[PDB]
Image 1 (cartoon, rainbow, N blue to C red):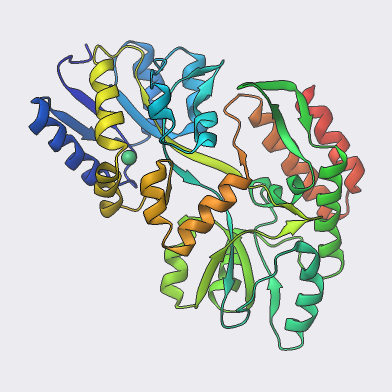
Image 2: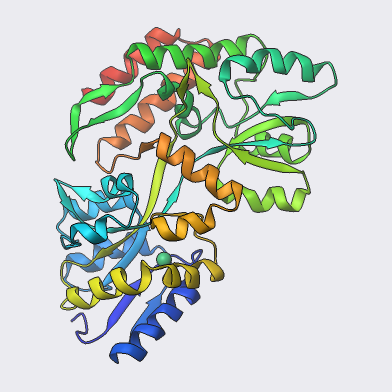
Length: 370
Ligand SMILES: [Xe]
C-alpha cells in the first residue's frame, strides 16, 4: 500500500521541507497530483525497515552514501534520466548515485570541506600546505596560530592524506574495486607524514578535536580551520571576519575532501515511479524548484549547473563546489565502514607516536582489504 495517484516524500527535518512542499504544490496545480512532504525522526533508519515490507515513501532524500545499503537490498528503483537531462548536472555528481553500475538516485546538492580563514589575521590564505609551518611561526610571534582543525576523525584529515595519491577504494568505469585500497601507498604516506611532522614541530596538537578547533577559530585564536558549511552559522554568530576558500595543495596536488551528495531515490515498491521522475526532473531539478527549497533552508552547492552558477556568486558556495570537484566522492559500499575505523586508528596512532606513519598505514591497509 504505497497510495498510487500521489507522491509521498521523506526528507530530513534540517532541510528545506517547507520549500520542497511549495514545489509539490506547483506540481499539483499543473497535474492535479498531490505531493505530501514528511520529515519523520530517524527516517534513514525507518526507510529500510518499511521499504523492506513494500511500504514507505515514493521518494526519499538523503546523503548518497546511505543509498548503497538501500540499493544493496533492492529498495531503490533504477532511475531513467536521458542523456540530455544527465547533461544538466555536473558529471561527477552522477558517480555518487550509481550502484552495481545502475543509477539509483538523482543528485541534488553537494557538500565538502573547505579552508576557512580569518581575513583580519590572514587576508591572504596559503595556497600550499608546505607554507603553513613558516606561517605558523610568524603568527606565533603575535600570539596566534596558523591552523587548527579536527585531527581525531579521518573525515577531516583525509584531504591532506589523499592529496598526493591516497584513496579509499579505486573507482574506474562506474564501479569500486573493493580489493584496490590506497591507504598505504606512497601518496598516503607522504600526506600523513606531513601531518605528523606538523604535530611534532608543534604547529598542531595531536589532541585537537572538533570542539577545540571550532572554539579556537571562532574566538580569533587561530587564523584558519578546515570545516564544512554546517559550521558557517556558528562563525556568523562569532562575528569573526571570515572567508571560505580552496583547500591548500600538497606537493602541488589539490587536497581531496570526501564529497557528500544529497540525493533523491525512488522506492522500488512505488507504483508512482513515472510521477516521481516527472516531479524530480522537471519540477525540483530546475532553477525555480531548487530556489524554492534553498529559500526555505540553504542547500549549499547544487548539482544543477544553471542554478549552481547563480549560487556561486557567494564565494563560500563557490569554494565548496571547487573543493568538491577536486575531492573524492564518498564510497557508497559497505567496506567503507572498515576504511573509517582502520584509518581513524592509523592517524591517531601516527599522531601520538604510538606507531610510525609507515606501520600505522601498513596496518590500516591490511585491515581494509582483509
Ligand atoms: Xe531537496
